[PDB]
Amino acid sequence: SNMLWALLRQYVRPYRWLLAVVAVLQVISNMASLYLPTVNAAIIDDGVAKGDTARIVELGAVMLGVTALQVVCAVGAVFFGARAATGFGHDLRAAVFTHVTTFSAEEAGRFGAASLLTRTTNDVGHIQQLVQLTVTMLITAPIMSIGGIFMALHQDAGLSWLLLVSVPVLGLANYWIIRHLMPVFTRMQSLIDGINRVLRDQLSGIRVIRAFAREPLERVRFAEANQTLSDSALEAGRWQALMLPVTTLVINVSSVALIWFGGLRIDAGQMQVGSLIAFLAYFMQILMAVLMATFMLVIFPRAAVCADRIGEVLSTQTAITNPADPVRPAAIAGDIGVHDATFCYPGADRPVLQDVSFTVPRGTTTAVVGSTGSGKSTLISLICRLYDVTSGSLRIDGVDVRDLDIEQLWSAIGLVPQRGYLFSGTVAENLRYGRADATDDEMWEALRVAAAADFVRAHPQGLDMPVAQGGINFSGGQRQRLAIARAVIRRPAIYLFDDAFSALDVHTDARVRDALREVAADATVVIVSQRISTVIEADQVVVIDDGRVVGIGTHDTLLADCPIYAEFAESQAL
Amino acid sequence: TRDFKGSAIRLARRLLPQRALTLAVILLGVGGIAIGVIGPRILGHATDLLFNGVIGRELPAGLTKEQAVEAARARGDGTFADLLSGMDIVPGQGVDFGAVGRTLALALGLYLVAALLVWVQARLLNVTVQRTMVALRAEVQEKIHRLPLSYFDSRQRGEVLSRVTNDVDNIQNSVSMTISQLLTSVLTVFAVLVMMLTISPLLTLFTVVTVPASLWVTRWITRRSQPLFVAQWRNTGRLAAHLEETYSGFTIVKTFGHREAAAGKFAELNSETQQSSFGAQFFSGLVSPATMFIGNLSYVAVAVVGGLQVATGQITLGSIQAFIQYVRQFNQPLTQVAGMYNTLQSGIASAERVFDLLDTEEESADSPRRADVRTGRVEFEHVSFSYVPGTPVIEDLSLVAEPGSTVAIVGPTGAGKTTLVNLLMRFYDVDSGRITIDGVDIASVSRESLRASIGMVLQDTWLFAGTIYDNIAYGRPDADEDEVIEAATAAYVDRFVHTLPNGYDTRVDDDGGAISAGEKQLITIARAVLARPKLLVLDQATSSVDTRTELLIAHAMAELRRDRTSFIIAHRLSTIRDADLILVMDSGRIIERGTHEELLARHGRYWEMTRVHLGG
Ligand SMILES: Nc1ncnc2c1ncn2[C@@H]1O[C@H](COP(=O)(O)OP(=O)(O)OP(=O)(O)O)[C@@H](O)[C@H]1O
Ligand SMILES: Nc1ncnc2c1ncn2[C@@H]1O[C@H](COP(=O)(O)OP(=O)(O)OP(=O)(O)O)[C@@H](O)[C@H]1O
Ligand SMILES: [Mg+2]
Ligand SMILES: [Mg+2]
């Protein structure tokens, strides 16, 4: 629970004065609640014993004032507690999001796009719940216990030994129960985590599960996880079921000892009768508050693990930032250098790109050809500066991508990745990610360029046709054409087609390429493709094998001098 | 919109089934509550005995109670005699500590019995709560496995995930956190009311005035707070949706310069959800102080009136002490219910969402017949299908596939090839017509066996978080190590696995890992081929795989492709060449079909498609 304290200390400091106001108001309210029985004892002693009804009425008015103070201070504490809890939760969420948005591809891949979502909302909620339950109930038990001890000492110090001995017994019993419960609760949380991951995997790959008839194995796995979770929860509940009886028993035994010892003191003229009522109410308030506070302690292990996850997210430091003072060329539209680039993924034993050196002149088309796992997508990601070169330099427009701020470099680059993603909403909304200010006319022009205008015009809603979460309401080629249209609507200086024509038929692929050549004539294009038929039109073709460039030149020189490209052409020949 | 009362009563019915264990739970709770409520009367009797002895000790022993009363009347202020009138002392006796000890021993025994009964009832409640939760989780998982694909395609993954896991966990927390409190409160209120009615009707009426007023205040607060709760839930859902869409497509958002817009939208949603949560939480927490205030007003009235009666002599002091204890033990359950109202409402909302998911329409009545392919011949007969009915995607389609024939499907980008092979796997219900494999309608056989008989390479590759060996063995986990190694070698997964320093043990994920798109497709191919399917479907199975590796893979799988009726979908004509039958479909209808030689001889769409390679 080291990370819990750090997170609370960091993100509750702006609300520390509201917390102090909550604390003082709760103290006042609990003091009023424990002082009402003192006024009852005063009625019993200075009233019916003396025979003064006027004193009884006066003390009733005093009790009315005490109750008014109690309700006012309770409402005032609830309001500020809610304020502080919601503020802490909102600030923690806004900090986690702001940290995650600075992550790189590798940093985000460390946790995943779903773990970050579950840590941004449900991990902050489980700590704001602790905040609220501490400013509402967990603070009541110490306040009520110490205040009741003081009030019992005030009423009659002779019988304060009871109230000072009974409370430690309850404290030790509840401490034993907590010490035997907390490991079980940690196990229950760590085991419900697994049954949640199982259900997430079952829903993310439902089509693959159905296609392979993996329903019975999924059922068996879920049944085993459910049974183990139920065993852990039953073991926790067996201990948790002792909390209320072991507190009520202490209250009742304390009350019986009260009636005995107070009676013994009363026979000696050392105690008034109303003190018995006062002490009885003190017991049934002090110990009931402790019981209520302790019964709720299902949060601390859960909050501890949630805070551990949040702190591990917030401790991750990015590796690709604007260096100190980025160079800002006007309208970057130049060439790509790639001089002796050497890249090795973090945690990898061997580099994936070795001694890569090829230049792409501005306004030309360069096709990257290689085997599976050769490093074409890695090179494309290097151009986008999603990853930083371990050695060498890239030199886009004659200047390193490292010293260029990555907002203008990305504004000058229109990238359609191999693993594309279409956001849920409308086709117009998805295309707006390219421009965000595009009119309907240029949106339709971008759709027409990417051959995506027909299947959007077909829908009765036109540009407002719905899009599923991952575009699963479209075909794969339709998703690729939508991504191409999104890249086109940007009108970027550099196009990076990372296998953007894999799911397009020959006719549609040729039409899209012709429209692009008509539109992107003045723009640099780097296209990663498998078909040789699409690479003759490229001015320069680069072949990479094992991660290193094995051939540079046009189609004819590569077919004549590079054995790998000759093998590719021979394999694809009809 | 959303019915919370019905979901609450359904959840209560699930929690407390027919009288097998819930009857014992209720009986134990009632017995313990009655035994523990009896005790304060005993304590009041002991206090009455102490006061009687103390008062009577001071009075002279030569006079009885009536003489003492008349002597006090002869004395001043009059009220002492009224106090003694209802006291029933024996003057000059003192306190009898033996009777006090007996009374307190009886109280201690009753309190011990009540504590034991409460413990047993709590254990039984825990057992039944866990049983109910197990049943709920099993039902949720079965419903997940029975839902149609349109249900998942029409919603975000995060929303369904939260409705499936987070809502169930919230329900579990709420029940195991509040069921015992609810039962104890509902029994204790009535037991205390009965014993207060036994003590004195006036003071118990004064105490019971609170319940109407407390209910009115609670109703007002709930009326003011329910819109806040629904707004908070809506706002949390919107925030979670925005977070999921930003995180899943982080590369696209970051690259296309939309990070600032996403940050601004998140800030707006965060502020709005903060406001909604603050309002809901404040109005939900306001219940307990109000109930405590009304209970304290009743306590003040009861104390004052009881003191007035005790001074007059109509009620003994021990009875009034018992009644004060009863007032406190009556006000406490209402305060506890008011305090836990927030958790109760959260659990009710979660149960509402879970029941909404569980009441969704399922696919269809699955046939119990086990699919059994004998030869492998596939036939389509006027198959018509359409997602979102009103726009056909496949209409008037008919095709025949010989048992050893390799059928290749080529066509435009939105023809319907994936829809066709999904209809073959019974992913979606065929609108009109039927599909027959070896003369039996696929709709008349179980989906499980039919989909197990066919090994399909999905167009969108998917891998679950685990080792590469686990992902390959996902097709058939019972296969031994040698079979998985052979499947990986045939698909040339082993070629790049040997390169990695943790071969077959490196952990890969759908969104990343130590893998590439081509290698991910290779692992999917190995997973498909491991299951030794009797029917082969390959939907753009090598779209991201180079042709040099494709040649080796084709040679390696030629043993399987000989006698398994492969369905090959590809936009590369080289892969689909030399297929026994080639289907060209344009807009969900097969415009032309035949082998390569006939297709070239008759010209048509295929000839134009293959002349693009030669240029024009
Ligand atoms: N939920 C859905 N899933 C898939 N297709 C859908 C869905 N709803 C509607 N459709 C429509 O179904 C049509 C049939 O396309 P299909 O999914 O069969 O792709 P395809 O012909 O295999 O394409 P490609 O060759 O690019 O893979 C598409 O035009 C698409 O708009
Ligand atoms: N985190 C990682 N992400 C991607 N590749 C990684 C990673 N770690 C290691 N690699 C290695 O990087 C190599 C090259 O991957 P990359 O995706 O760049 O290849 P590629 O030739 O572009 O792929 P494909 O032809 O399938 O599109 C792979 O062989 C893989 O083992
Ligand atoms: Mg790639
Ligand atoms: Mg498809």
Image (spheres, coloured by chain):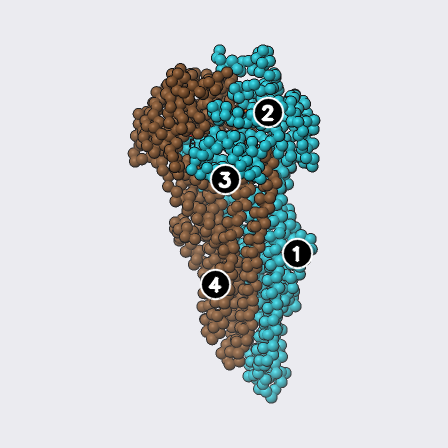
> SS class of the residue under badge 2?
helix
* Residue B170 position within the rendered picture, expressed as x and y whole percent measured from the top left: 55, 48
Question: Vertical placement of B440 versus B311: above or below?
Answer: above
Quadrant for ligand 1 reads top right
Outermost bottom residue = B62
Give the labeled residue for mark 1: B22
What chain does mark 3 sit on? B
Name the residue located 55 percent from the left edge and 27 percent from the top edge: B557
> SS class of the residue under badge 4?
helix
Please name which of the two marks, 2 or 4, marks the residue nearer to the observer.
Answer: 2
Outermost front residue = B482
Mark 3 → mark 4, Cα distance in angstroms: 52 Å
Please name which of the two marks, 1 or 4, marks the residue nearer to the observer.
Answer: 1
| Drawing shade for chain A | brown
* Residue B73 position within the rendered picture, expressed as x and y whole percent measured from the top left: 59, 81
Mark 2 → mark 4, Cα distance in angstroms: 82 Å
Within 10 angstroms of label 1, few (less than 14), some, or many (20 or more) residues?
Answer: some
Within 10 angstroms of label 4, few (less than 14), some, or many (20 or more) residues?
Answer: many
> SS class of the residue under badge 3?
strand
Give the labeled residue for mark 2: B562
Tell which chain the image draws in cyan: B
Give the labeled residue for mark 3: B466
Within 10 angstroms of label 3, few (less than 14), some, or many (20 or more) residues?
Answer: some
Q: Amino acid at mark 3?
A: Gly
